[PDB]
Amino acid sequence: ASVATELRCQCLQTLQGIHPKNIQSVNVKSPGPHCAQTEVIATLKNGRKACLNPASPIVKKIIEKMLNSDKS
Amino acid sequence: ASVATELRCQCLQTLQGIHPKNIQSVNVKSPGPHCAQTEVIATLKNGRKACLNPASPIVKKIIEKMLNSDKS
């Protein structure tokens, strides 16, 4: 028994590039429905998720650094 | 009634940067469990998903281009 908002989305409050170690992945979507906003959720190691500001510089790192860590 | 493999994962067969229009987002995960492989799933507009080779050059574009499309 509750009311649903017309946004819903999933971002917490877009953090400014937190530290990884837990951060195992991330998702990036575009606007469309009433959320009409981007999407930038970093799935935490425990299977959680956070949103960050890709427009942010440090956070734009979060994408690139999350992209890094390969060629093992 | 069926048997489960020891990989499961989700990747289709990592495409080499397909065309967007439908592609609305993507997810990028790292190795860990028996899948022990990366993750690069582009969620389709219809709410589907595909995997692509980020090691691939065209596909490394798929990440950057998916990153593009903002500042509206």
Image (cartoon, coloured by chain):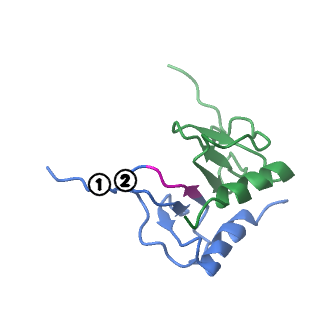
Chain colours: A green, B blue
| Pick the front one: B13 or B48 | B13
- Disc with the residue nearer the chain's start (1 vs 2): 1
Residue B71 position in % (x across, y down): 85, 59
Number of numbered markers:
2
Q: Which residue lies furthest to the front in this view?
A: A72
Q: Which mark is residue B6?
A: 1
Residue B4 position in % (x across, y down): 23, 53
Q: Mark 2 lies on which chain?
A: B
Mark 1 touches mark 2? (CB < 8 Å): yes
| Residue range of the region highlighted in magenta in the rendering | B27-32
B29 in the magenta segment: yes
Rendered residue at 67%/75% (across/down): B61
Residue A23 position in % (x across, y down): 62, 44
The 10 Å Cα crowd at callout 1, few under 14, some 14 to 19, many 20 or more, is few
Rendered residue at 51%/60% (across/down): B38
Q: Mark 1 lies on which chain?
A: B
- Quadrant the C terminus of chain A occupies: bottom right
Q: Residue furthest left?
A: B1
Identify residue type, mark 1: Glu
**Label 2, on which residue?**
B34
